[PDB]
Amino acid sequence: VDYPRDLIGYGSNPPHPHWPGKARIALSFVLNYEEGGERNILHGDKESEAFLSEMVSAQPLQGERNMSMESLYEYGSRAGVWRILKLFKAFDIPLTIFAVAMAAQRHPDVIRAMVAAGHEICSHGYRWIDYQYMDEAQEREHMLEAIRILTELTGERPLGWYTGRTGPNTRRLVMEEGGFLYDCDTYDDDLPYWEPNNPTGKPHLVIPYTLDTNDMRFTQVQGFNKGDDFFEYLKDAFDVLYAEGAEAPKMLSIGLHCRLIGRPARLAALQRFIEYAKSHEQVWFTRRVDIARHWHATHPYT
Amino acid sequence: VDYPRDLIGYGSNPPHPHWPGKARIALSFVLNYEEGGERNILHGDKESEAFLSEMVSAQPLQGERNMSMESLYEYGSRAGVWRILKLFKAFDIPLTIFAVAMAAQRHPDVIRAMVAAGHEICSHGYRWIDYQYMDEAQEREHMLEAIRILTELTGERPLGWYTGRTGPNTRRLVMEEGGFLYDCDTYDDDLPYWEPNNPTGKPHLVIPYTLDTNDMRFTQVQGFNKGDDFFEYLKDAFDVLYAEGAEAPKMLSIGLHCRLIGRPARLAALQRFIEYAKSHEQVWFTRRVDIARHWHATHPYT
Amino acid sequence: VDYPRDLIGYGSNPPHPHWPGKARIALSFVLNYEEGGERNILHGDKESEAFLSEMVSAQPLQGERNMSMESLYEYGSRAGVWRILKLFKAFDIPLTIFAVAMAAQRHPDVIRAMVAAGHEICSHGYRWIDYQYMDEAQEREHMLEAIRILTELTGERPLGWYTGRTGPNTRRLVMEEGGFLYDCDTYDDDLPYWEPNNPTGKPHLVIPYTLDTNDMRFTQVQGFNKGDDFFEYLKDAFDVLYAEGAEAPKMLSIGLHCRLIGRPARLAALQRFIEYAKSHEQVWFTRRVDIARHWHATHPYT
Amino acid sequence: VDYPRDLIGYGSNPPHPHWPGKARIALSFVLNYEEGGERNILHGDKESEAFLSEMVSAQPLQGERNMSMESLYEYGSRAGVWRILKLFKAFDIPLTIFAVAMAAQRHPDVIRAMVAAGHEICSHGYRWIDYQYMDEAQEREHMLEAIRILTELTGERPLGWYTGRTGPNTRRLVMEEGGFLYDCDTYDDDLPYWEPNNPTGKPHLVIPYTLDTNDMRFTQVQGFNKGDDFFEYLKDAFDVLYAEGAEAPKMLSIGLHCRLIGRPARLAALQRFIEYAKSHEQVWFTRRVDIARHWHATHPYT
């Protein structure tokens, strides 16, 4: 029937990306910047934050502040962020930053640092909250606001979007806005593709993200006990994709959070994966906007 | 008393299967095909899907679409399925496909591919949902429909059944239908056996399945952190059974899901287990319908 | 105040057990036999079983049968039990069986086998259910019944007790009954001790059990991914205790369940631990009734 | 806006601690002493304890005693505590004890032992309960009481505080009391810092604690399967911090609980980490009050 999902996509025939330097794989390291934008009555929310912290079994507290939860988030913005940024600078690997606009407003100096470092600032929404149930009017308003904030902060408007906890209208509103080159609000492929259902009809690129090669699993019910578990997980993902890349190259995202991989216990394994990746020839270490411009120039929208 | 369960089965005296090629073990690799058939208001369900995805702590959403959940499922049908099918083709190992009829209707080309590859299409029900509470009338109707769909799709009716989340009537309805050679809706033995309580009185073979040597544990609360955990789990299962097989051969199922082992990070470990298994002599790599026909010819129903 | 718990016990001065053969450690392997006695409307319960199976996130179903859950339990009594019993017979290690009386009634042949093998049959209660909220009258009645059943089944009354999910009266009722040598309904020490609060005033020995060196963790939210995790856990427990045993020997329990360690994937690691343990001199492999009689003869109740 | 959190802290410019012996890292091993102070109707609570035990999926029981839960806690005070104290004595490493005042009242002999051993007794609150919702009046009263108890018990008032499950007023009340040198009710940095918002205006030192390099994860939903997982986690944390310490030394806390790392299976890995740490030059093994006095003398409050 007139089924609004594409279960098929490229089928058994995915396109060759032709990554620069004849790369057998494209690696997109992504650093989320959410600290200061999460759930909090201080921010006008009805409850405290519970998602993604050391407090693995936390529940949101209605009309309350959860001090421990707040403090675990402050680790991300106070200490984790700088240690991570230094690590990427040390191996000369660029980042795409998934920056929440309210978080960035609260820490403009680190955002400025990131931009000066040459990292791409991608929009991660106005607030770090669940958009599942929000009215279309308000989600659109948050969106246009996130754009305003990041443009002023950065001096350049965001060209990609990623909400994460999206609702039924999130991605439609992104493509309707007009000014995005891409979005990342899918986990459906190993390659970019042109959105098949853009009402706008303009080319809109989808660059799928990840929930599995993602440090969020360090704090979820099912998830890595020690750093080496995340290293072996990342390593396996690389090995299979790199092997496929001998004839059919693909991409791999690596999701990271300041308050999570920022802890020394977890950073070690990220550095190990980076050294592993760097030891291979034909790896394209890149930003998602660069993948997007590359797609345009290589596989233009027909 | 007149207890409707058989807690005893074969007791301390299990039969020798006499697998072809004097195999010390029979390996049944199974690939579930559920993507497109899962919970969704689009499919007429009251809520979204929450079982078996990267969103380890998901809950069903009433009257809502969960876009992320949908997208994680689309990974299975868009990308995972082809990579898995290639892996099995590369080692010349046949599959039994646990194909959900609605999922197959949404992707007939992949089903046709599987059949052309020589994989057995086993019925996994009309829909991928919990049958626990469904009225007998409707479950029977789903069943006869699943049969209709797969016969047209495949050109041959399904000879095995597996629902998974069965209710008190599921298995009785399967045996009452008449045309199945076997079912897999048990986790009670290491060997096939004839159903002791078939009202039909015709021979009905039970080929027990698994929830432990099953990639579903990658996304459950208790479950594998990294691929090597699933490899060592599978390897241990093999080692003990193979050792028993010197005098008393048995079988082992390996359950797989497109949207799960389809991810590169997880495929590596499956390939490692396959290489391990292949390095042993006297291993029978087979389909469940072949086990069933073998049982008939070897241990006829008395 | 008049605090009904002993937080202190032996303090920094635990007694030397003087295990036979000058053992530096006493190992108590325990095999639970619960299959056939668990929650089930068939057994007169209000709901199905959910504790300790592959269905890691199961909930009890009110007025329903959970067929999968039943089938996972049937694995324990049909297949797991024999494989485990063979393993212990192969290394000549004796068991204490934690036998639920209703489970034993449903499978008398395996109970008879265990007794003929020389394993101790310890009482694990009439039913495998939570006694937390049961009235004293009914719990006492279950208890006297469990005794009746096992005596007839075995030809000798049970000399130890272990309920597991006890209520505020469980242990008091056990000691009031009179005929038990010991109970195991604590997790409070590394050595046996005489119950300090027996109203009876007769000597009653407490032999603490375990929830950590216990295969139940294979199916709990926090718990072993692969067999080697349970092997390394057991190995570490052994190493520290054995080292302490150079001057101050203690004991270690290893809890096992037919439907859990009975799976080949998990048995491998148990066999590895047994081989490790066996490779050490001065290890006392024993039954809990033997520890109890030893305590009597070695550290009589003053 | 006038946002009551400091998301920024030291920014990219953390101070050099100048640890004694030119240490590249400061290690604070912490032993919680909570057993006897946890939730219990015996203690006047409305429900039993459920946090941090082998009963990984426990829920609090209203108006009930949970005997197993109690017994698992008694392991901590009866057996775990002495084994842990011996381990630290063997490597000549000092502890900071996070002692709950009610727990200490129930076991004065072990507290006296700890003090005689030269370990610092830090206040962990009057009771081991959640202060999230307690009225300010009662939390203040608990606090002044915890102080009274520990001073009498120890012969010296506590100079640090740590509640853990704090409410919106906990830390403010601590600094208002006047007599504390520091608190540990944050998880926001890798270095001590002066509280920027002390109403008192006196210098108050914050020495951040941890929920990740903490044996509590052995019994949480996401957490270590085997001891080596905690060893590798601790080792990684050390390696990254020690490497940073070549130019910019920091500190690392290691949280421990008697009833958890007290089990032999878990102690092994703690001993392994201690041997690893000890094998490095320039490691400062210290107590938190010593870090605090050092901070005063080295980075006085301006």
Image (cartoon, coloured by chain):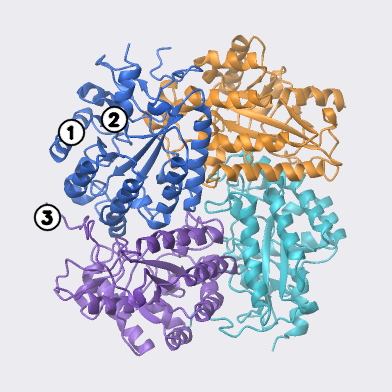
Chain colours: A orange, B cyan, C purple, D blue
Q: Are marks 2 and 1 in contact (CB under 8 Å)?
A: no
Which residue in the structure is indicated by mark 1? D147
Give the residue at x 38% y 62%: C241
Which residue in the structure is indicated by mark 3? C2
Q: For the residue labelled by badge 3, is the local secondary structure a helix, a strand or a loop?
A: loop
Q: Position of residue A252 (x, y in %)?
A: 71, 36
- Name the quadrant of the N terminus of chain D: top left
Q: Please name which of the two marks, 2 or 3, marks the residue nearer to the observer.
A: 2
Give the residue at x 73% y 52%: B103
The residue nearer to you, when weighing D83 against A284, is D83
Q: Is residue C201 left or right of residue C219?
A: left
Q: Chain of mark 2?
A: D
Residue C99 shows in the view? no
Q: For the residue labelled by badge 1, is the local secondary structure a helix, a strand or a loop?
A: helix
User: How far separated are the C-alphas under marks 1 and 3?
Assistant: 24 Å
Are dots 1 and 3 on a single chain? Answer: no
Residue B181 shows in the view? yes
Closer to the chain start, of discs 2 and 1, is: 1
Q: Please name which of the two marks, 1 or 3, marks the residue nearer to the observer.
A: 1
Q: Position of residue B229 (x, y in %)?
A: 61, 54
The residue nearer to you, when weighing B173 against B171, is B171
- Name the quadrant of the C terminus of chain D: top left
Which residue in the structure is indicated by mark 2? D289
Q: Chain of mark 3?
A: C
Give the residue at x 47% y 22%: A78
Are dots 2 and 1 on a single chain? Answer: yes
Identify which amino acid the numbered label 2 is placed on: Val
